[PDB]
Image (cartoon, rainbow over all chains, first blue to last red; front, side, top):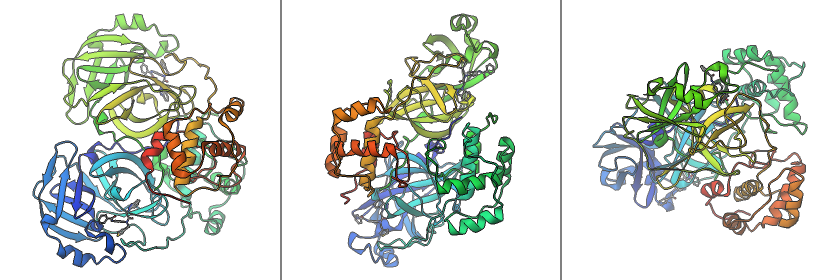
Length: 306
Length: 306
Ligand SMILES: O=C(Nc1ccc(N(Cc2ccsc2)C(=O)Cn2nnc3ccccc32)cc1)c1ccccc1
Ligand SMILES: O=C(Nc1ccc(N(Cc2ccsc2)C(=O)Cn2nnc3ccccc32)cc1)c1ccccc1
């Protein structure tokens, strides 16, 4: 038992991290087969950060402009033989395939989805943590400018699913990046201008999963006979910065295991949002919305007890 | 900017995880050079878990009693050629040295220290997370029964420092294990009996470090001119389940960078302990005490807030 933020083991991703340098700027890249991916803003000189013309920047560079180095493991300097833009990514073709390329896929995750982040600095892995794609398609991470190129991923049956490359800090502790098709998560441009974020929202179904985790972990004081219909909850959610609830099979099975109904949990959310009354749930006095039902499922399998 | 629970990258440790089976019990082991470590309760029949005779169990086992397999990466079946007891651990000697043994050390951490955990199941790494050794030398982690043998570690300069091997769950969300000298953390025996947990406390210096991280991230509402001397706080701490504050250079450094004195932070603690007044710090409405000063140092290095 217990519930903690858990990341996928990072070894397979660590073997793919490299350092990329262009002019005075350096950050991290991801080396898969004969390709190195990094943010295109590596090309931008410090004085043009507000107004980058990436098309001009691209063609002002030669292949030799980009120095690519592998520092950890089987150390190497990698010759760049082509460079092109893929949305807000630079795609550097190099003359050697990464022999440690894992089986992999690319995906774009949806708000409410969790993934692991390998934080990197100067081409070396430095930390691992998990985030959730926020309703406004930001993430709440921990980064420096030198951490750009850090990689978000999930893992399933030996296959690494690459979903995020770190691009920018939008505001304090608020970050965004692109999927590997080069599309930036959310309504955000890779430039150094104030950009307004859409309002964030609690991910209801994640909150519900977390409350079920709590109940399986013996924490149940918040469960009452009180029920709220999904239609009534969703109307309330629109006025209180929660997402609308749509049930899933995974939630249904958690309800089955605990004997606590979805309508009870939605009622608990409404009460708890008004206040925790000096009490805690799984160590917290705020609603937790970054565990998905799948994340919870992985960490439970106890019999409901009490 | 941003502050998240960060773990050390796990790849170096992943290469050392194996599966160990004895009779019908299987769990995880750590393979370094020609040695495999695992909890000694792998020898115990299900029906003797209340009062195992580990010395008699050891004698009844042969080297052939133990099946060790590497299931990930370079797969292997490892032949056991010796077995001996090391406190609450078994030390198996195998006939093949792990070719991927990292530079490593062993140490035993003190209450208030953080370390990373690679959760494993049937000899396969499954997840990474960070814990803090509690005041009663338990940890608040996330483990299932097949997770025994999972490994706790830190990184120090390309050296893996192994500090924990998971042994048991004491109560919901409460765990302990041993260092690799085979000494169990805390007052706990490796038998299936209810054991008394000494009362936990808030680690004051960690809470202080967390408050400093908040200020460095532009969260400052809790800072007042109010001060409380160290000697006075410590008197207060004894009656309110906080550890005594002893100053360190790391904390002094944070105080200097933020211009907020330790005494102001201890005052904030006394106040926040009474209640957060409907406000939040770094997203939370409870005092966070599992970030060490060094954990915080590594995630800060932005420049001046007001
Ligand atoms: O510093 C340099 N470049 C740079 C690049 C990107 C950013 N932006 C905004 C942006 C995106 C596209 S254009 C501008 C971030 O959000 C970088 N970033 N990303 N995560 C960060 C966390 C903390 C601080 C900064 C962080 C800022 C600066 C530099 C250094 C030497 C030579 C040339 C350039
Ligand atoms: O299940 C078996 N053994 C076993 C071993 C240890 C434990 N204990 C307690 C303990 C310690 C020393 S002796 C007894 C835990 O705390 C295991 N543990 N460790 N972390 C856990 C999290 C959730 C549930 C259980 C967890 C429980 C059972 C088994 C299965 C087949 C054949 C023989 C034995």
